[PDB]
Image: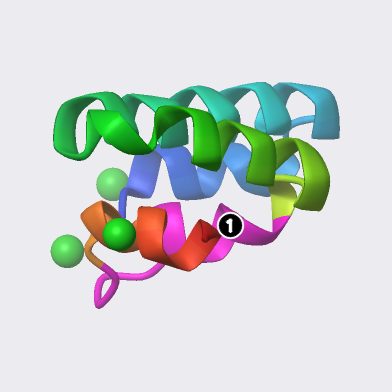
Amino acid sequence: GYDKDLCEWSMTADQTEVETQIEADIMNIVKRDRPEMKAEVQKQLKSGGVMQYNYVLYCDKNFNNKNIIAEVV
Ligand SMILES: [Cl-]
Ligand SMILES: [Cl-]
Ligand SMILES: [Cl-]
């Protein structure tokens, strides 16, 4: 998705803060949209990291964030 607020904020916030934000947002997407994938997505975020999803989640109008679950797994 594209969100001016989170896109601009994430571009200059420290890495620990952006990581916390992305991880929270991805697990919230899972909770709302495909709650049965919680354990699998959580383990994949721990194994692969979360910073790689910054662009698609916040700075990309063409990405529907519901599709982050398929992106992660
Ligand atoms: Cl504005
Ligand atoms: Cl938009
Ligand atoms: Cl899926």
Task: Identify the residue at image location x=66%, y=22%.
Answer: 20
Indicate yes or no whether the magenta region holds residue 70.
Answer: no
Segment colored magenta: 52-63
Give the answer, above or below, for where 14 lies relative to 64.
above
Q: Nearer the viewer, residue 14 or 52?
A: 52
Classify residue 12 by image quadrant.
Answer: top right
Task: Identify the residue at image location x=28%, y=32%.
Answer: 36
Task: Identify the residue at image location x=83%, y=34%.
Answer: 15
Dot 1: element: helix
The residue indicated by pointer 1 is: 53
Task: Identify the residue at image location x=52%, y=60%.
Answer: 73
Locate residue 3, reporting x and y percent: 31, 49
Left or right of 68, for residue 72: right
Task: Report the amino acid beneath label 1.
Answer: Tyr
Locate residue 41, reporting x and y percent: 52, 41
Left or right of 23, for residue 66: left
**Residue 27, can we see it?**
yes
- Where the N terminus falls, by quadrant? bottom left
On the rendering, which quadrant does ligand 2 occupy?
bottom left
Q: Residue furthest bottom?
A: 62
